[PDB]
Amino acid sequence: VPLDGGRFATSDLNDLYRRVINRNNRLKRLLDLAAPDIIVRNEKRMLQEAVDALLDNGRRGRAITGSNKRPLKSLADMIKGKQGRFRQNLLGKRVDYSGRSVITVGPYLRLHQCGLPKKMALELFKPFIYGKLELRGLATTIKAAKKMVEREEAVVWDILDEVIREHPVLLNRAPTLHRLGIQAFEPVLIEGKAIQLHPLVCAAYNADFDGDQMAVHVPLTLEAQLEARALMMSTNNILSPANGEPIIVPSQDVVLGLYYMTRDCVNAKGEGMVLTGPKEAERLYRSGLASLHARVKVRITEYEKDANGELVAKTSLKDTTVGRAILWMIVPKGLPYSIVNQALGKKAISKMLNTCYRILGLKPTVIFADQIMYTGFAYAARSGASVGIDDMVIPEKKHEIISEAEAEVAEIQEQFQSGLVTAGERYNKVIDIWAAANDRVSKAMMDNLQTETVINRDGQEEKQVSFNSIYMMADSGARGSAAQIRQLAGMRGLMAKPDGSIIETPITANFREGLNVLQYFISTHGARKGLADTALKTANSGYLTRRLVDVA
Amino acid sequence: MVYSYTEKKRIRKDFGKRPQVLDVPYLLSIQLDSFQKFIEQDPEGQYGLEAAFRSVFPIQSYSGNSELQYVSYRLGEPVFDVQECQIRGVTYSAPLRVKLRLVIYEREAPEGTVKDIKEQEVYMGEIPLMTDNGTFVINGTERVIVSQLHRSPGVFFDSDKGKTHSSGKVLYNARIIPYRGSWLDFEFDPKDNLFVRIDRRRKLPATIILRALNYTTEQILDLFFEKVIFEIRDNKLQMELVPERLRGETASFDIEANGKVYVEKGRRITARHIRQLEKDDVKLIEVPVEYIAGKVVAKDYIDESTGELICAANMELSLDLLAKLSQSGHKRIETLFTNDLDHGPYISETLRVDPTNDRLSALVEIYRMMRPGEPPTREAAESLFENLFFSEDRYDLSAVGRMKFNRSLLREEIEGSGILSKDDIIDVMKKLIDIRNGKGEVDDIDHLGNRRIRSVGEMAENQFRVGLVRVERAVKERLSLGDLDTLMPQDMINAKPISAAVKEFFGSSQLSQFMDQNNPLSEITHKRRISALGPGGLTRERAGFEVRDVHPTHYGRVCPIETPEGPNIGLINSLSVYAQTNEYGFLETPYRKVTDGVVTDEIHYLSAIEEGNYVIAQANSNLDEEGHFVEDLVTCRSKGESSLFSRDQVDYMDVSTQQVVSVGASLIPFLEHDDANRALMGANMQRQAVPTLRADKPLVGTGMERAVAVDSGVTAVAKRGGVVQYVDASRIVIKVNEDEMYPGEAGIDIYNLTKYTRSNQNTCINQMPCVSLGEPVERGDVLADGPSTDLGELALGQNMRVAFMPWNGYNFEDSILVSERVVQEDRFTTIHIQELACVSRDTKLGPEEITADIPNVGEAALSKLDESGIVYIGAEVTGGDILVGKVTPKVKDSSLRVPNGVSGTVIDVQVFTRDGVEKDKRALEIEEMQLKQAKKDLSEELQILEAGLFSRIRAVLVAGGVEAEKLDKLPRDRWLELGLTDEEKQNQLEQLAEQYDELKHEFEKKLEAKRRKITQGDDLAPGVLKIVKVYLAVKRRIQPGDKMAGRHGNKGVISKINPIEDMPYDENGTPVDIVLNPLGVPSRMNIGQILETHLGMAAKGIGDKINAMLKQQQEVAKLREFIQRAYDLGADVRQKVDLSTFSDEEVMRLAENLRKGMPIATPVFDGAKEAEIKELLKLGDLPTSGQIRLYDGRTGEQFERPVTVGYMYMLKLNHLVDDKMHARSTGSYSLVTQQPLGGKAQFGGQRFGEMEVWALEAYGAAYTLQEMLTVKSDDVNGRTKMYKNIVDGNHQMEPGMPESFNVLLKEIRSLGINIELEDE
Amino acid sequence: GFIGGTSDRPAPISDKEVDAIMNRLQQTLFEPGEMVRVNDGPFADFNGVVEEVDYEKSRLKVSVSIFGRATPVELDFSQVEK
DNA sequence: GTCCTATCGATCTTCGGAAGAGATTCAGAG
DNA sequence: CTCTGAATCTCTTCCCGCGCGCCGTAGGAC
């Protein structure tokens, strides 16, 4: 192929063939002219080595090159290799009718929908649009149809809104480790340029929306559309194939919303009255006459399907909370009330959803999941559960727990100052005392976090579970488990050297307080070790996957 | 305390506590001081091009009997300055001229020369130069060469467990690494046999070297072993005993004499036994013949009578041998000390493995194993051995290498020659054997005391040396074969090898990084970057956890946080703030010299190796303002270990809390409160921010900006103090005060500010003024703010008012909700300057043309084209418009149409044309415009200078015969002989008149040269006739999909541009701009985001109070009264400011620059505690809680429980969506295999990888796969029949067969393989 | 280096081989209709066709494609490219 | 200058990869 | 005298997308 200007791009095989042809022609010329035996032997050796370079360049003593020691690729080089035909062009090949974009979360989408930009839709569904312009008779042929599509005529958008009506699109974030990484979605046009993805699906893709690109492929033929809708649709993949675990496990924010909504407080506005039904409860809340966490008695009605399969309606008075009575308006008509009569968290909600799939079926389950997501988002917005430095609590006894524990190490040092202990025993006593101190600090911090709430119930103070922002985040299982709140409010604790040795002097600070220079330098050891561990293991995992697929 | 005028506009409140004793040094001196050490000539020829030449010249031909020797080199000035060279696209370099003296001696006579020819600095090559910003211009493209970090030359000892044979034992191996020459490695075999190798060749016996060194087995054994003596006097074989040789060991045999027996058989030996023995004079002792039999003799002993070998070196003795040899007349036997734990036989074991005999044998074996296929020869094996390790051409320990080597051998002297010596190798072997006995310790390879930094001025020197070596190789032969008579030194050499070598280094080396000019911070953090990669280093795919992980000696020299996480973590590092390179190349850092009990103000730099010899106090220790440690005991680090030590025991103290971090991490406030992972992400992201359109300031910074923005080289800085005279947003002219005015020079300094110019990331880099007409300035003040800088302080982004709360899920776990107000204010809009070129070549069928008369085109697209065929400047264009009317011969409509998607304003068109071909009309107009501008610039310079000069002349004529009538009578130029007495005033007038005449001629010559340059037909190098450059400005706004980020590792794409109504508002009605997510604060341990935010609130609150006090016409006394209170608040802070001295003019001026929030400084590890944030919030009427209640704009309800609201500094990262959204229906297809092209700049489709194929196979989708891999991509006939059916509305495919597979078949059939399809 | 059986000892050539080499060191008609290229001159390396035979003058005459015609152009003998 | 032939056909290609397994050579002895 | 051990050699393997940027036969003879 030529390049910019009157030059043709260098071709490796062409040059290998050129070398071989020149050497062989020289050998023929000599054999015609009867060159001495020594010369013809040398020419024959050179010809053999040139054929060697043409075939499997590199198996020679040294590969030949025509550049800055960049050896030329041979035929065997083109056959095998990660850039070879097998893994570069046959097993995986670039496909038309595809694109990519930066994704963003659209909470309004249904589970089976996804939003795509108008521009990407127009540039992917071009032939379908032509297939309407002739069928509508609005365009004469392709020559005018393409021009009209270029004209982005306002009628062309009506054509797109008709073409895209029921045509699935495949969305494929990469790296797609498991089959749940490729799914079909019914598209809806969106003004912007980002791909609107559903919240509940992002868990399956492991898709954090911090600038994560994702690709779309348009299934063209009829069987392709049917296969997408029947096998790869979002609603057809609610269970994980690796274990009996839903892949629609509720997101981090939604579970926070449900945890905030169904929780109960000791004394609250609108407490103790009797509500005639969930609707009246909801009205009360929206009129502001009652608090969401208020304790109340609402008449609940539930349906239980018999062993044969017909629902039996039973109605009763139930002691519950206003939030639970509101949520009960969303749970389908087949479940017991005991699932919503508890403060739901990322675990407790999950089994709930599973039970729905266990009883009602797929079709009730998907709509129930969407409704749970909607309600969770709305009431989490109403919660306004902000986080601030005022919310990170240092237990007051911590300074004492340090002041004693360090002193004990001093005693372990004093023995070492007296020759009464060995070298190793001093180390393994100091580190154990520090670990016990870390446990005490963490226990006091957790106890203070849960104890920070005490309220008056019409008389005499009584304690209860804490509405502390960090506590609700941890307890709901959204983000920030015990090991996180412990580092944020207890002490950072011990650390390890790159050789793994336990630091005799733990990081006695926590991130709410300032860490000093040496403490931070100690922390860098673990931080970089973890980052390097990730960067190196992300490759061995993939290689193991390839070996497994190619053996099975 | 005195505040500079640039500083005396916004007195940023500082929360620091420690007094900064050492200000941050120049941040780019790492580059400049090296290239300065390179280009500068030096009588100590070392460290420069003169060193490279003296390492080559003089050069002589032994057969020639004549030499040529280097005399001197003088560097010609660059032909084009940085700006012109960047515009045209050439490299910025200087011509090297070298004086060569060719001396021809004479045969049959002493070296008295017949003739010597000194060439007048013959041309040698073009060497690139380092621009004052620290960057090289190579092809218009601006490059930065990263300083490399690699193992220092010397000797290194290493051993490992498990990695070798896993059998518990460790193998000790030593390596000698010269600066330029062959590696030499000594190693122990698993059976304790010592061998050597060169360049990791095959194992050869170690002692063969000594045979090559001409050592007899007797000499070697004496060198390495100890002698134990037996005598045949006074008794049969009494032994000379050294009692200390017996210790710990059980005395396994009888030894008794002289009364008391010291130790009997079967018992150990202790010290008191040694004392009794020493009292006993054990010079002779009784041992049985069996003990004498186990020894091994030290020397050859022949039969004295027959002259035949009866004993030899390393021969093991026995009873009969003893009797025989003593009978032969050798009554004094000497054997080797071979204590197993103490005196191992390793050398003797090598003797047992040695198949070679002597020096001839040594050379034979060395030659055969070094060069298989090459026959040995006595005269030739020396030619190999000496060149291996003794000849300068192939061995040179650098000065740093020799210093490190002598340090490893504990020598008293470090100044030694570069070639190894016999005792030098002997000492290396001795240290190796001692380490094998365990009496030493192995070194750490990844220890900053073993790895040294090479910079540009050294790698370039090495490349120049390589070029000169090739040139010498050629010209030695030329002089040997040349007739030496008609030859001249220009004939001897040709520039091509040297020029090619240096050109390759500066153009395509692995370390010639293309500069990432995103903003001033990216430039700085890229110029001070340290790399472990590159030639002579390791590779990203062959490095393990050992080299990546941080090190206890990295403290104070290398930032442990700022590393490019991903494929090459830990291999690319950023040099610490204060660290600097030692003379030898190691990294040294300054520490405050602690004297006994006081911390003095004396800074001594300690390197990575010296630091272990001291005890260093941490910079956070308190002192009593007398220098004494307030704490009785202070935490210090000694040998990597850190622990408490008593006061007045410490020896040094770190100079500042920022000594551990780099600039990228130094700019992050509250770095102490962020987990190191989020710190790393924030530090990496901070250099990706795009310069916004109206970047202002950070409310909460760390004070490091006042240096980063100055040393970045992007802001216009006042060279000297003076008063501004004229500003027009392009050229600021300063009347430099006479205190620094040169007596004859103009005394008035211009500053031509650079306007909108494309950067390496297609961004605009225009500089805008900030000083006012008549404002006084002092040398070093920032006159014009560059991009991302404002009022001399670095400002990457905008401070948006953010709230932490879930809001209907639009901020779901990474997403960001942004009010429409911020996009209405153009907070984040930024300009992108794209460069599109339309080339035209003299094709084989004829020369191409650029014309508005393009064939096959209507006037609709020509509307934007001119009469010549180029777009009018300032016309707004979109994708698809024709910008250039090029035509190709034989006709074709090849013309530049705007690329799809992009749209903007055409702001610049530079047409470079090869001469000979006629210039198009618009090119003529542009050239005339350039010429008019150049003439106007030169004329304005000369005329303003003439005004100043004539005014100075009239001022001289004030005293000395002032005559107003005769002064205004004639024109001012006819003042050659104005009335003035015979004094020195007429001398000053004559001096300045000669100066004016010189200025006249200089104006003339510069104008003519500039006209010739501009009119020059630009060199279109390869067979090309003309090129048209076009520059497009795109004002990209912010849209969903764009990526924004804080300074705390918080990042996310904006998910919705929420209208103003839907945003929450507080009880004052002010709506928040950005709604962030709360659930992220804990999980990602970045609680810094919610102290800064709190502080930010207070930082605005003070401004909110000032603005009212400025909006309400408060009296200045009260305004000052408030502001001073806002400044004096806090602890005993380092910064103290008394606004009283501001005369109310600077008070009002400060307020006008403070009404938008008082900037606050929170140093990295000397930052503000929460108690001060609470105090500052208390100063405002803001809640001391930090959290406010908000109201939902849609429903008017109040959110339950208050929420955190504040002013977080947010940055728009350079990853906007419009550069990444792409979709393809049909277009280009590749040639060899018909699969669609791949990429964005090419209309390509996404690659369907193997993992996607596996996932499709996981479902039962087979039709989907068949389509995806046959019709969509590969089957050429099928994909058209599919296209037709889809247009027809049939939706049916005919797959056929993927062409690529057929290609594969041909590729296998081209071999000796017949692979074919089968029917059944 | 030399060409021989082993690098330790390169071998001579032969007795008769030297003599044969010293022996040699001491010791195409333009057909009508044939297509040739010019060897030198402004028409060198062009697709031409022989039109007639200028034999006895040690010359040549080959048709060329100039002006869109197969114009009669005459050349020297040493302009052949067979 | 263009147009041709050919590869360090008087060097020294980079030592800063692990590893995992076959293949190919060498011991202690039947 | 060469049979089963090891012992030392060579050959082969190392996630995946995206997006820029640049750089891309040489010497000497007619």
Image (spheres, coloured by chain):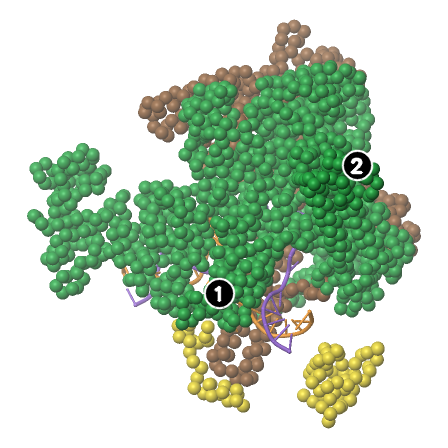
Chain colours: A brown, B green, C yellow, D orange, E purple
Discs 2/1, front:
2
> Please, which residue is most extreme toward the bottom here?
C56
Q: Which mark is residue B26?
A: none
The residue that mark 2 highlights is B963
Res. B103 mark: 1
Residue C49 screen position, x and y as percent: 76, 83
What residue type is disc 2 on? Glu
For residue A535, side relative to residue C80 (left or right): left
- Residue type for callout 1: Val
> Label 2 vs label 1: CA separation?
69 Å
- Report in which chain the residue with disc 1 lies: B
Q: Can see residue A232?
A: no
User: Badge 1: few (under 14), some or many (20 or more) residues near its Cα, within 10 Å?
Assistant: many
Q: Indicate the chain on which mark 2 is placed.
A: B
- Give the x, y percent position of residue B868: 86, 57
Task: Have a look at marks 2 and 1 and say if they share a chain.
Answer: yes
Res A413 seen here: yes
Mark 2 or mark 1, earlier in chain: 1
Question: Tag 1's secondary structure?
Answer: strand
For this orientation, the residue located farthest to the front is B982
Residue B543 spot, x, y in % from top left: 51, 46
Q: Which residue occupies 42% across, 35% down?
A: B612
Q: Is residue A123 left or right of residue B161?
A: right
Q: Pointers 2 and 1 in contact (CB under 8 A)? A: no
Identify which residue is drawn at 73% across, 30% down. B775
The image quarter containing residue A366 is top right
> Residue B437 versus residue B995: which sits nearer the camera?
B995
Q: Residue B1064: give x, y in percent of width and height.
A: 77, 24
